[PDB]
Image (cartoon, rainbow, N blue to C red; front, side, top):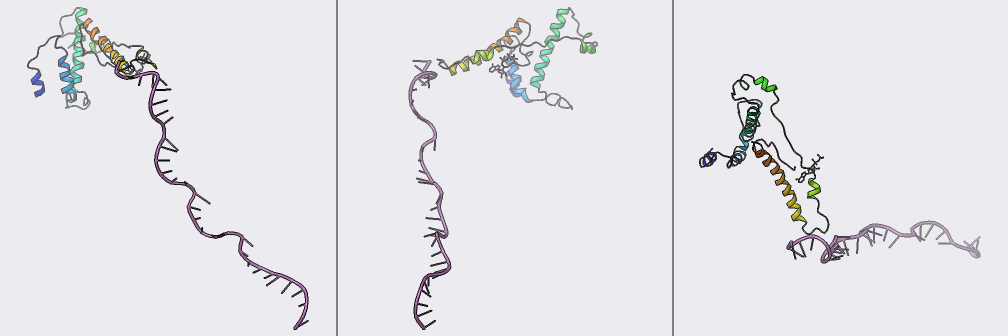
Length: 152
RNA sequence: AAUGGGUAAUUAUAGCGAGCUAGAAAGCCAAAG
Ligand SMILES: Nc1ncnc2c1ncn2[C@@H]1O[C@H](COP(=O)(O)OP(=O)(O)OP(=O)(O)O)[C@@H](O)[C@H]1O
């Protein structure tokens, strides 16, 4: 808690610093549970649970501000079981193809052998990173919605 | 007693039965670019 209070003080809430706050949770709160007085939710960390809750809560707003509603107590608080059945979320994805054809393009008599092998598998890691972080600001979203990123 | 003859046994016994050092190096290539 003192690690939180030292870095939450001198801090600004904007898209410039929309992303340093997430690592402040994903490092510090990475092992702290959520709602410990329970019988089922024993393993959902507060770094992940706050990351998913902020991921959904933006997507309700982009689902509702496009349909044209402005009040939030009749389609959320009373029509909760209707929203439990209402399809309101996409699970997007992507798949970067041709990764090993690009990484393992090394051959005998390659003038840079291991440096190009360590660069190309890092290059496609940033490319798989930038496909995420450029789709989210083309939209109105950010790194909470990205549930995973890996090898493509 | 003379005289005629040799007869049987053993045919090697007990051990050691290989030990240690080396078990692929240097180039090409790749690296350095
Ligand atoms: N960035 C990466 N670096 C290293 N290895 C990777 C990377 N991305 C994927 N791989 C490895 O390559 C395998 C498959 O990669 P591939 O490019 O065939 O994916 P894919 O095209 O989605 O395959 P499929 O068409 O069968 O779904 C994975 O099992 C993974 O181990």
